[PDB]
Image (tube, helix red, strand yellow):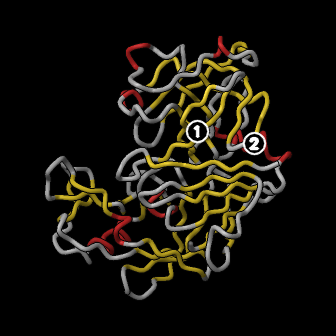
Amino acid sequence: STGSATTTPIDSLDDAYITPVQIGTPAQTLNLDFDTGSSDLWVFSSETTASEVDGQTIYTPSKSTTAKLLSGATWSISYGDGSSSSGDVYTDTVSVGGLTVTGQAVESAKKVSSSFTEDSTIDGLLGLAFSTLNTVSPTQQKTFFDNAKASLDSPVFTADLGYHAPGTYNFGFIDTTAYTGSITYTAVSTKQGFWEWTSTGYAVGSGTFKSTSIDGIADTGTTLLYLPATVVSAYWAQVSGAKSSSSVGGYVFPCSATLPSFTFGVGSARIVIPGDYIDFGPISTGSSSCFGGIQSSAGIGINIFGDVALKAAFVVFNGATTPTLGFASK
């Protein structure tokens, strides 16, 4: 089997992407944030504290003839950005782009933090990291991909995120029309539960490539590109007037700037992030200070190849017995 679903930016900045997901019988379609940096499929629901729901579409398990309470199971998750959610668990039928999993753990939120409430466009998350990170207790649950994998034509999924445009998540096949040139595959460590890999270096604009190993995670659920302070300083030094602002929470730059591109290495291959992808717009409405899309990972504890990086590539998440990651230009 295979599946193919369009993923759509939630706003004009590509802050996140939503993908429609069918849950239950009859289907209840929710727009979920597919997150290769976590491993829980959770939804706003009829159980979510009413004051914490503001415009989201909810899953109502009592209206699904295939929903079953997973007795005694609870979940609770905290994300890198400080947001969180928790609740109880149902199993139900879940379909993405025509690919159906029966008995998927659907984690129903009883509580969500303010950032989730305030984002009316995201109805929940669908985790695509390794199932070892799944938070369900006392019996850990499998991700949608893990459940689907054996049925798939090939044990892979691909992320093809758009810049200010829709893109695609495919399951079970590689669309050879969706990228240019060849796909370069690179080793993955699953030791921390992430799609963790090592970039071979970087360049700023038309500058020379610096060969240096940068360990990090391919994370569709993180907006920006978070890299070591040395790398980030080298980038922003090429933008007149750019500076790190403790008050704003990262590098800012004059909105009048033309940003240079940023290149990262995948083996001997190179992925080029155009400068425009690095512009996250005014820090506040009407400001002439703009927020940068490349930020320091110092104090996160890990480098993160988030959407800014991934949307410059066609990315293969190869879930074979020994997982790997593939990157192609597009």
| Label 2–label 1 contact, CB within 8 A | no
Q: Is residue 261 left or right of residue 100?
A: left
Measure the C-alpha gap from mark 2 to mark 1. 12 Å
Point out which mark residue 20 bears. Answer: 1
Residue plotted at (71% across, 36% down):
95
Q: Quadrant of residue 76?
A: top right
Q: Quadrant of residue 132?
A: top right
155 in relation to 256, above or below = above
Q: Residue furthest front?
A: 26
Secondary structure at numbered mark 1: strand
State the residue position of label 2: 99
Q: Amino acid at mark 1?
A: Pro
- Report crowding for label 1: few under 14, some 14 to 19, many 20 or more residues within 10 A (C-alpha): many
31 in relation to 254, above or below = above
Point out which mark residue 227 bears. Answer: none
Q: Amino acid at mark 2?
A: Leu
Q: Residue furthest bottom?
A: 208
Q: Quadrant of residue 42?
A: top right
Expressed as whole percent of the image width and height from the top left, the position of residue 240 reads: 18, 75
